[PDB]
Length: 99
Length: 49
Length: 99
Image 1 (cartoon, rainbow over the protein chains, first blue to last red):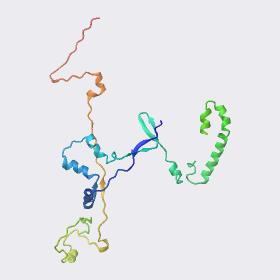
Image 2: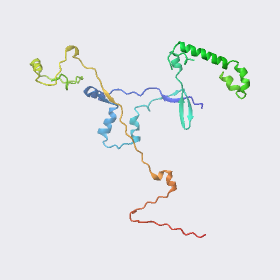
Image 3: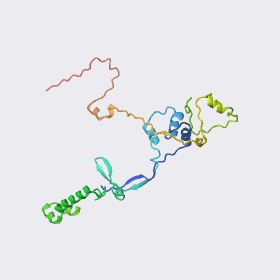
Image 4: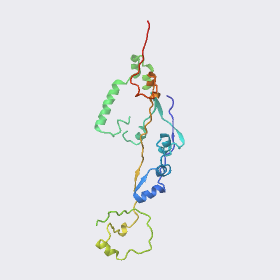
């Protein structure tokens, strides 16, 4: 199947320590991942009944915002699933390590 | 093949290399002559070799 | 008492207090006047390293609704809503065929 290409993100999703995390880090030795989400859920909109579509921006921490780039690796269609197939043998043959 | 040589050279690995020398020597020499008996395997065997 | 009980050496941004607290502090430290006290010698008299544990996520199972009327099993049935079902003792369907 002549595809041998995928569109992927060019960078990691950044998570950094903000000041609101930092006061909890110094004061109690705890940080919570994306504190702002929890505070917006608790103190701003109290009820906000649990919904998948509402939480879809929350669960992805900027992974969807990344720019795309072409990636070279072949795929096969196992039934309905287009699955990528590759090897990593050459980068270990370069270093004389067991694969 | 780096699979056989990944652990460096040792007595057992050298011996298995000699055994596979013997195997491939008996089996895949004069491959084009053995292509006659295969019949329907005309192209794919020569391409693989 | 014991040296470190509630003594947390985290680098809190302390307040500056004008009053003096060192009046007979050594002898009061010797007797045990105030509990949960630590003496920090000068080589360990520093801001501590900052450490934390992190809650990476909280995720909840979201249960989708399933309607009988939207599954194809109801092809094999005819669904009539019946307002007062308890009032019916028995229903009856009678077939008259001439051959």
